[PDB]
Length: 124
Ligand SMILES: Nc1cccc2[nH]cnc12
Ligand SMILES: [Cl-]
Ligand SMILES: [Cl-]
Ligand SMILES: [Zn+2]
Ligand SMILES: [Zn+2]
Image 1: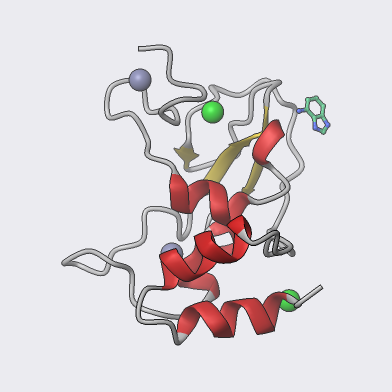
Image 2: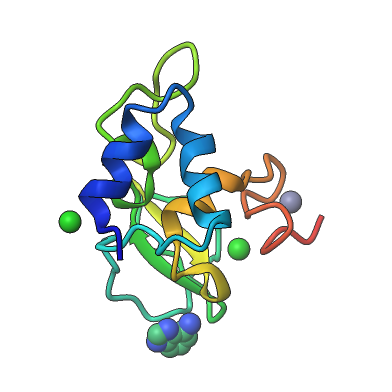
């Protein structure tokens, strides 16, 4: 395995950190590990990003910042404000994707209607 520090350093100093990690994953690289898994009942709302763990039976709940490429790389977030959607919150990851929470949050978008992940929880 490359190891978390080797992967995160490679992405952090890349001109495009998101593309560096996606290309690394596509190459067969081991996902970033040591995301902070939360103790929960799996009876929550199943919403994507929440003040407290909200995993349903089809999700795992994690500490938000631990699942954010930009937080883990200690680099600026790519928006005008440099605001992080995940920091200080809990993130629900479909169990089928929970081996790679950083890649999941990087690649996916929260539905502004139901507040669930588009293409997963979202039933709009
Ligand atoms: N997705 C899940 C549902 C119920 C229990 C579980 N323990 C770990 N993941 C779980
Ligand atoms: Cl580590
Ligand atoms: Cl979901
Ligand atoms: Zn972040
Ligand atoms: Zn929706």
